[PDB]
Length: 130
Length: 129
Ligand SMILES: Nc1ncnc2c1ncn2[C@@H]1O[C@H](COP(=O)(O)OP(=O)(O)OP(=O)(O)O)[C@@H](O)[C@H]1O
Ligand SMILES: Nc1ncnc2c1ncn2[C@@H]1O[C@H](COP(=O)(O)OP(=O)(O)OP(=O)(O)O)[C@@H](O)[C@H]1O
Image (cartoon, rainbow over the protein chains, first blue to last red):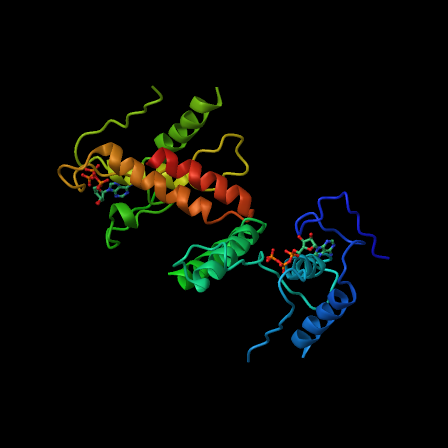
């Protein structure tokens, strides 16, 4: 049941469930990603011409994996989608990944309830960042 | 009854219970200290040189640093400051703060809740800074 509302904004940000043109792909891509972790580089590619809806499709995959965090036995954490065109011209991708990964780790550090657990893992994270 | 062993070292650090001489003053000073805060809270221990002031004042801190739970009033005592063994130009406020900071840092490292530890640590360092 895919119902496209033409008078809706119909933008990658505003696209939700039940009006995603690509839904069989989204369902099967998530399962393939999960199975590759349950069992080197593990890189998936989603191809398509310009305007095919890559940004709309890949955001749903991040949304699909983010939902039901603890419920799924295989746990995958998704960083926010990186857009190479909107990044600074000379800013490295490894810097972008770490900066987004650091915030995800940092917000988890602020979520602990044990002082020693938070204190010990904070310096380990800072040691690797250094 | 107090028994002094002349073959013992008989030093301020090597004086224990039943060997300390002025227990009557020590017992009534610790209680007097406790009632002073249960209600310029400065007490003075007078004595001529060689009367045993260091031995007496070490026991008062030793007595006040035990069985804190039973007594209604809780007093935390810094290690005794000897003004003659400090550096010549170091202010007393620096010496007191540097010893107050350690026990606080030992208390912060003793917490279990990570949120309480974080909030107090930045509050403490704000005063220190
Ligand atoms: N599932 C969908 N439901 C409704 N409209 C869609 C859907 N997928 C794509 N569209 C429409 O097609 C357009 C294609 O834009 P989209 O960003 O998804 O594609 P892209 O060209 O691969 O990405 P980018 O903007 O990053 O270049 C959207 O702006 C939207 O108007
Ligand atoms: N309670 C005590 N029991 C036994 N001997 C004591 C006692 N108090 C003092 N003395 C004896 O007197 C000596 C000097 O004591 P203490 O060091 O306390 O003297 P003070 O002059 O008050 O202080 P300071 O040593 O800092 O000048 C001890 O080393 C010991 O020989």
